[PDB]
Image (cartoon, rainbow, N blue to C red; front, side, top):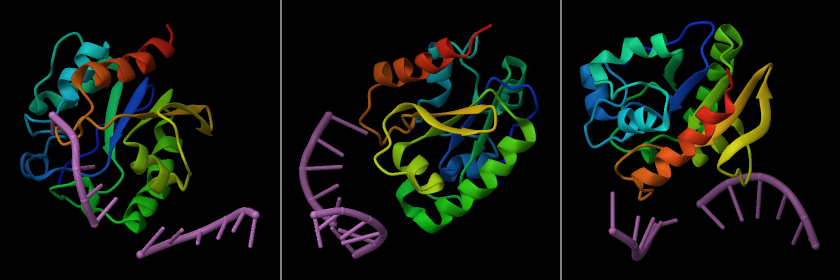
Length: 165
DNA sequence: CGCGAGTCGCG
C-alpha cells in the first residue's frame, strides 16, 4: 500500500493511475527505476535535484504532493477498469476540496477521461476546475509510454511555468 | 441523425 503525500498550500498534487507492483511493495510512489516521474519533475523544475522514491515525503518541501486515482496495485494501468477509475475520481475530488492545491495534475489522458467522465480531452490545462484548483492532464511517466523524456519534461515544465510566484 | 459503448502496433 502506497501512502498519499498531501497537505494544504501545495502548488501541485500529482495523481497517477494506480501504484505499480514495486511501488506497492516499497510503499513509495513511482518506485520502479524504469519510471520517469522523479527525473521528469526534477528536470521540469519542481525539485532542485532528482529525489529517490524513498525521499517522497520531502515533496511537501517543494510544495508538491502525490496521490493516485486507484489504490489497488497492478502491473499495467490498463488492468484498472473504468469503473474503478470513475470511483477514484469521486474520492480524488474530496481530497482536492480538502487540501486545495493550486493545481491537480492527472497523469494520463485516459485516466482523466475515466476518472472525470470527460470526452476527447486534450493534453495540458483543462477548463474543468475543482473550486480554485485548476486541472491539468500530463503524460504518464511510465516506461511503457512511448512518449520521450524530452516530451515528458516539456509537458510538465509548462505546468510549472504556469503556477506563478 | 445522435448517442453510448464494443483491440493493435508503436521504443
